[PDB]
Structure formats: C-alpha cells, structure tokens
Image (tube, rainbow, N blue to C red):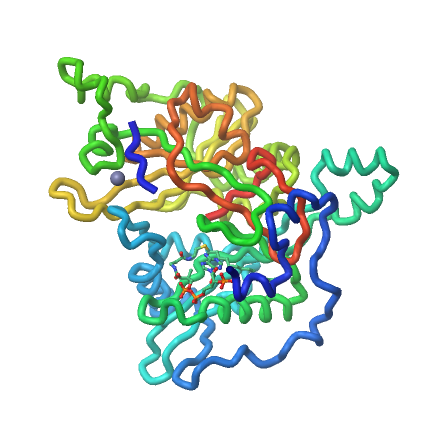
Length: 417
Ligand SMILES: CCCCCCCCCCCCCC(=O)SCCNC(=O)CCNC(=O)[C@H](O)C(C)(C)COP(=O)(O)OP(=O)(O)OC[C@H]1O[C@@H](n2cnc3c(N)ncnc32)[C@H](O)[C@@H]1OP(=O)(O)O
Ligand SMILES: [Zn+2]
C-alpha cells in the first residue's frame, strides 16, 4: 500500500573498477592501485581557496559537534523535493562517528576563515572488515589450482568507512566534493590505510553489491495521512477501509519470546560471540571487539535499541534497531516520522522471523511508525511473512582501491548508514 515515487570527470581517475562489466569479471579480491607507502603521500593538505581553511572538529566539544549538526541539518539533503527530511541528532552523530579508537583526523571539514562558518564535511571511521575473495570464487579458484592467490587477502583488514559527505548548498556543483574525497584519501593514506568502504543511493563506479529498501508499516493510519502510504482501491470497497487497513498491519502488543529484555553491559561478551558466529557466515562482514559491540549495540536512548533473549543464564538471541526520524513537510497533523532501521541480530534458539516479529512489536510499543531495512544479511527471508513491502530506494555498496567480484546483498553482513 506504499506510495511509490522515484561521464565521470573525477571518478574515472580513481582506483575503483570503472564499469559494471569490469566488476562482473573480477575473480580475486585485491588492491587496485600500485603499492605505496605513507612517505609517498603529500604532507600538506590539498589546496583550497584562501578564504577557506581545513578544520578538524573536536567531537567532545559542544560547539564543534553543534557546528557539524547544523551543517548536516541544513544541507545533508539527498532530495529537496521529498516530503521528508532525515534528522541526525548530535547523539546519533557521536554514535556514528566516534566509535572506540576513532581517528579525529578522519573527520574532515572546510570552514570559512573570516567567520569560521562550516561549509563542507566528510567523515571516516575505522572498521575491521573481512573482504577477501568470496567463498564461491575461492572454491572455484582452488579447483583451478589458484587457491593461495584466492585466499591471499582473507585476514580481516583495518580500513576506513566513509559517510556524511556534505557540501553546503551555497557551494554546490563547484567540484568541492572531489576535493573532500581527495583530502580524506590523503589523510587516511597517511594513517597507513589504503581501502575504504562506503554506501550511496546514487550509482557510481562501481558497486560490488546493491540492495533494495523494504518497509514495514507500524502506524498505518499515520503513514497514509502523511502520504508515505496509500490506501489502495480495493479498500475503497470495504465498510471502514481505514479500520480494515489498521487490522491488516496489526501486531501483538507484547513480544512472543519469554526472556526477552533490554541488552545490558554485562551481555556484551556473549552478544559479541553469537553475532560474530553469525556474521562470519557472510563473504563481506565486520569484526567487532567487546568495546565495539558495547559502543554500537548498547541501548542509547533516541539512537540505538537492543534486546536480548536470555531464557535463564545464557544470551541465545538478540536484535537491535536504530532510529532516524524524518521531518514531514507541510502536514497539518504530523511533523515527524519515527523510523526504526533494522541493525544487527543473531538467532540461535528461535526462527529468525519470530525474533524480528518481536523487533516489530517492541519498535511499535516504543512509538515507531515504520520499520525500514535493506535486504542484506538474511533480511530478505522474512519480508513476506512479516509484511514488509519494497521501497523505491537502493543502497549501493562500494570499495575504494579494492578489486572485488559482484556479489548479492545477501552476501553482505556490514550494516552501513
Ligand atoms: C583509502 C581511503 C579512501 C577514502 C575515500 C573513499 C571514497 C569516498 C567516496 C564518497 C562516499 C560518500 C558516502 C556518503 O556520504 S553518501 C551521501 C552523500 N551526501 C549527500 O547526499 C548530502 C547532500 N549532497 C551533497 O552534499 C552534495 O551534492 C555532494 C557532496 C554529495 C556532492 O557535491 P556537489 O553536488 O557540490 O558536486 P561537486 O561538483 O562538488 O562534485 C561532483 C562529483 O561528485 C560526485 N559525487 C556526487 N555525489 C557523490 C556521492 N554521494 N559519493 C561520491 N561521489 C559523489 C559526482 O559523481 C561528481 O564526480 P564525477 O561524476 O564528475 O566523477
Ligand atoms: Zn508521488
């Protein structure tokens, strides 16, 4: 019942595969660029106009995080004609940008010298990623006798995740974005890191995986009244069509699993174990320490919500979801849309659809209006029984400086904003 509404001067110089045809022919994982060392990377920041300066924000400082908050609030807009606007609170931004061992230098900003107004931003965070040759390719490579080349890059790699690329609207379409990407590349290279991973809605050279978005209505009445959803014509036959619509997406009001409770700090080592056990099944996936599990998964009000199944003693299952609220433009009754995004999870004692059913119940009980996700992990497996519908977006996954075969999004275990 959803409302469906839908030459590279810089990227052709970058160490990424340049065509879909190239990517579909890659058989081994490995770097694109020729080997470099840190000393081969320019010491000085990339030149920008004299009215501007590079600035590294201190995220512990109120003024700095507020400055980044305001830039993104007013300028981090994928579509000016959308009826919605994503909102990234300072707490959200600290959670996304300041994981344990984050590198301040990788938060790259441009500001105007005279008044110190922040005009552009791009952010990298460390992540440890398994990104060696997909298991099927390695298998096929072994049958041809090339197993050790296929396995050469199997060790998890300490790399960079790039997000929150943003140019102030006054500075748009002036090639500042390539400069931001070059400066981040420079700074990351100077840390002896040579690959990055990143996601985008736009199609760039060249994704290794792409996945459709899916939505699960939690407050159908509100979703229709803001035109996120429509009430289709067959409902225009029934007696109280809106009552019929609310009945169709009705959930139980209390979760089905006993032992389900909010995650607490003492759960961290066990959640790490069952998560890692699950994520290692996928060709591309992160490796998390206890500190990273704690930072990314411990409940964080207004940002991250995480529950465990602990039916006496042992943590056997868990799920998590994070919040991004959308401003609703021009609606008399509603100003905000509260969206729950499926995060990490692991099921070992109950079917996956049963665990995610409880996610929906908990998310609904916490006032969320819609539950969103991309078809990574095993998310595709419960779409139909839990009444998710596909949206119009696609999340495209890219590597920088990494030759990588084309894979399915169900082969990807890295949750990325
Ligand atoms: C080893 C370490 C490596 C580190 C770096 C790894 C790579 C990181 C890569 C970045 C990962 C980002 C992940 C996220 O955060 S995805 C979210 C992106 N941000 C937004 O959508 C916020 C709103 N939009 C904006 O702020 C601007 O429109 C941006 C900044 C996006 C472009 O600014 P502007 O509109 O003023 O344009 P320009 O004249 O300066 O530049 C035009 C050039 O920019 C290319 N472009 C456009 N959109 C994107 C995009 N989303 N990723 C990469 N490149 C993009 C475009 O194809 C063209 O290149 P080419 O077509 O001529 O070749
Ligand atoms: Zn429309």
